[PDB]
Amino acid sequence: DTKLLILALERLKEAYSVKSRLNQSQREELGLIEQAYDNPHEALSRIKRHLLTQRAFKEVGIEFMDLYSHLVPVYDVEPLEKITDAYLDQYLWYEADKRRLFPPWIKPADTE
Amino acid sequence: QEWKIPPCISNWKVHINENFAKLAEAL
Amino acid sequence: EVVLHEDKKYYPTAEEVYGPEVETIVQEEDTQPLTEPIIKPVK
Amino acid sequence: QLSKQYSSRDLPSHTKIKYRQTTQDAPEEVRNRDFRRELEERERAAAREKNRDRWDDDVVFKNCAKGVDDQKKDKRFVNDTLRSEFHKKFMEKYIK
Amino acid sequence: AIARQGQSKDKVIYSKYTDLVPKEVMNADDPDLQRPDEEAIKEITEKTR
Amino acid sequence: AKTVTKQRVESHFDLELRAAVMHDILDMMPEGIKQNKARTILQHLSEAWRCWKANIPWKVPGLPTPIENMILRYVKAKADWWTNTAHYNRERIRRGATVDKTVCKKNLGRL
Amino acid sequence: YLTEHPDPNNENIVGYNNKKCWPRDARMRLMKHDVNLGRAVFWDIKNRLPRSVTTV
Amino acid sequence: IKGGVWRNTEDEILKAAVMKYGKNQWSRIASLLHRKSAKQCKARWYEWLDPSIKKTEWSREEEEKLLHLAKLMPTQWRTIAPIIGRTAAQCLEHYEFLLDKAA
Amino acid sequence: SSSESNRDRRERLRQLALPYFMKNHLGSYECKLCLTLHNNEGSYLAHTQGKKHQTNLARRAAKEAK
Amino acid sequence: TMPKPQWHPPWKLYRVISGHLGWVRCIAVEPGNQWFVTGSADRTIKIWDLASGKLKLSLTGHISTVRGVIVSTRSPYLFSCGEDKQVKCWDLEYNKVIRHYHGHLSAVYGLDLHPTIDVLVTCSRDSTARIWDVRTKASVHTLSGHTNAVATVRCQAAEPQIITGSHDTTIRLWDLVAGKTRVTLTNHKKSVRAVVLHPRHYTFASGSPDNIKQWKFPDGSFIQNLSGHNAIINTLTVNSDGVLVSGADNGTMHLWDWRTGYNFQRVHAAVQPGSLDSESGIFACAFDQSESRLLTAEADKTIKVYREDDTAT
Amino acid sequence: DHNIADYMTAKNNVVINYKDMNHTNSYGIIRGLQFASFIVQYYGLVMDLLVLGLHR
Ligand SMILES: [Zn+2]
């Protein structure tokens, strides 16, 4: 579990790595992720609690990155649900690879 | 009276189909 | 019956609303591409 | 009290007036013409032109693409900016 | 005479009720309504020009 | 004799839209005899236009139907102008002709 | 394919896409057997995907 | 760090602020409160404090409708909540209450 | 200093929404019915916006009407 | 009536042409029935084959809505004017603008050509109208006068050369060479949006939301009052056959006997396939040279062509 | 586990906000979710099973 949570948290930290003064919400995100390093078991239990219960989340921001040809959707979530979802993802992919869920023909693959 | 105009005080300045039932119960 | 949002008609056929007697044609683009003269000069 | 100020735009240009010529369609011709006959015959010609012009033993699904002949959605013109087919195409193209 | 006061006698100004009230018909045509003529137009046009 | 220009065009179009509606309807709607809701009808205009920008259906509980069909008409016109402008600008940027700092962000917001 | 979609005028070659980046000798030739084999393929694939699910 | 429990003082001041400034300006309302952000103020308005929200017991019809719909569209609370006229969190709590008291 | 603006703004907001609330010879806010003292008028107002403050006005209402 | 007067055949809708993206505000027809032109909010001017109804040519160059369009008779020009402020002269020999007439302070609502002199007359929101020397691009005269926006202006050869009306509800008749008013008519209660001069009679008509008045020439004696159809009416147009057409903002169109005010037909026309019911009504309309076709410009972004019904009686 | 499923799904049902605009997404999947990838690839596996057919 610690392995997974660590990976996901690093991933989240990687978007802000250049780190200008950012903003308020982003500040909340860095402080909360930073919190997750100090007391991991807390974060893991809170996460599993969400996954067992909450069916209603908060509103996601949306904005368009401009490639000058086709626009790219961009979504913004509150940090709590981002850490929760992130761990959910590292875990899902891990179990998935262990159990050989995806046959080889699907190739945005880690190997190559 | 007819040409009373509601003041435009500014704020700046749902139904469902039953096919969902058939589908969901089917699954 | 069911219609995907891919189609889903809104508004009747163009022709239907006006009726049969009138001819309804949608000109888009154009013809006689511009280098042509409306009013052609004498020679 | 007229000012000695000038401007670039104002200066002479196209001082001659192009009068219409006889084959361009001088008013003389127009007065004499029977338009109605001309308009009818042209119309008829146009109409005529138009006339001239015209295993897998295993699968989930039997053919979906049976009678699906495109439909006249691009023949309909719609006077509504958000439901014009042009707008749909634009919206389709530029958002992801 | 109030209204004219500023202007010269020559320049017209409607004021009486009679002016307002309708006048009827005039037939299919009468010399009364017609476009000055060719020749009046030529004179006017030339002087104007 | 100031000449329409890029800086002034959006302001120009809305100026002469406010005038278009004003002359038309106050010469069209009337019999208020005193002043009929000119400030107010125009505030209904801007209100409706914001609502269509937010994609919020806009229904005023009381209102004369000629006033409502009015606003819906002109608002749809301005919507057609704004939208067509948006398409055109995305075509220009796509081809990479225009380099401007503002039209990119604006055009983005539109799409 | 020709059973459900006939082409008596051989119009299957009108809207077929080739890759024009390549030189002519490298670009794909246009022939009835070949083109129609192509559209028959693409059509066969498409009919295995219900339109409401996804499409091509 | 900003997150925390909602206070009667913060909640009443939120009432007054929303009354004065209007619904669409959140940054202005978050400016007055301490230890709360604009997102939190908005979602706190529309989730709970909003007077249009219905706080009371569920009638029999609302329970029939809620159960039927929840069996129709599993796990979708933001779709169902407007149909029954209740808050998503509220109808959630009531649903887990119906399965909780049902056995 | 930004903190100073909030104090000013939260007094005026509790003045608008405001007949019982006052300010003593000191700066504190007080409810003259309930004789309670409030740290901030808004904080005080909530007590002023509370259901207990409500009652004690009604009780004094009756107690006078008798 | 005189005696259940002048039987005219009804008209039917013949053809509908799409292909503007904005409201079509203006239709004009070329001197030889070859091509008819349209101005639009789209900012284009399009030229259409009268016969087939196919689009010949799209011009671009106005910055804002084109409001008014005239095709000169004696010279191969378009004139157009817009909400932009700009009045342009296009040489149809090259399909480009050769001159531009500068000087109104606001949108120009309307314009017209003197039939023999070579002078252009324009109306603007700024309450003036101008007489422009086509050849030198020069404000010959400025017609001060009305208190609101001038809407429709017509030009004639004989006496009162310039006939104009405005949103201030009063018509002034302008003596061209003086650039002063000879006659003020004040008999409409609401804005005068349209006027029209009768081909042969030496009379003229004006339309307001309330009703439509005919006038004697000169000096505008009152003559008749056609009452019937009440809308904000944007178009009045007349055939040599004495057929007067009234357009309107609510979509309605009525045909009138010029002589009597007998309103023989009422046409209410379907809005376009998409569209909305409210975007109905005809901004303007015109008659080909043969008097055999009536063309209308509509807010549903179409052009409709009406044809006189041959079975009729 | 059914819980994980109900979480993942229930997440795709939320409110999209941009300035003025708010709406509910009851149908399309949200790409920007952290775990959206796994949904995409799995669903894609399903449609693959359609295209290739189970035997092949
Ligand atoms: Zn108290």
Image (spheres, rainbow, N blue to C red):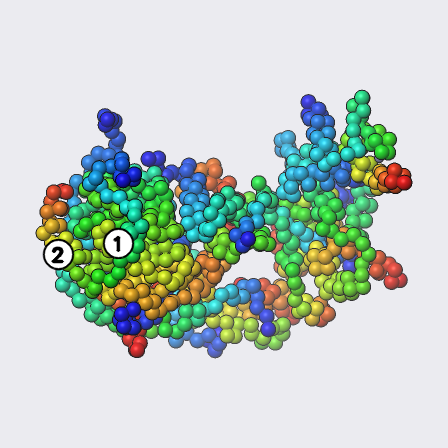
Query: At numbered mark 2, what does the secondary structure look like: helix, strand or loop?
Result: loop
Name the residue rendered at 41%, 41% in the picture. Answer: F12
- Disc number at residue E6? none
**Front residue of B15 and J143:** J143
User: Compared to H61, does A44 lie above or below?
Assistant: above
Name the residue rendered at 18%, 62% in the picture. Answer: E29
Q: Is residue H47 in sight in this rendering? A: no
Asked if disc 1 is less than 8 Å from ligand 1, the answer is no
**Front residue of A84 and J50:** J50
Q: Is residue H86 left or right of residue J224?
A: right
What x and y, as percent, mark residue J58?
32, 54
For residue H91, what is the image quadrant? bottom right
Name the residue carrying label 1.
J221
Name the residue rendered at 50%, 43% in the picture. Answer: F39
What x and y, as percent, mark residue F76?
48, 53
Residue type indicated by callout 2? Thr
Q: CA distance from mark 2 to mark 1?
A: 41 Å
Name the residue rendered at 45%, 64% in the picture. Answer: J273
Q: Residue furthest front?
A: E1
Q: Is residue E43 in sight in this rendering? A: yes
What x and y, as percent, mark residue J266?
38, 67
- Name the quarter showing ligand 1: top right
Mark 1 chain: J
Q: Residues within 10 Å of mark 2 (few under 14, many from 20)?
A: few
Residue type indicated by callout 1? Ser
- Disc number at residue D22? 2
Query: At numbered mark 1, what does the secondary structure look like: helix, strand or loop?
Result: loop
Mark 2 chain: D
Q: Residues within 10 Å of mark 1 (few under 14, many from 20)?
A: some
User: Compared to J299, does B27 lie above or below?
Assistant: below
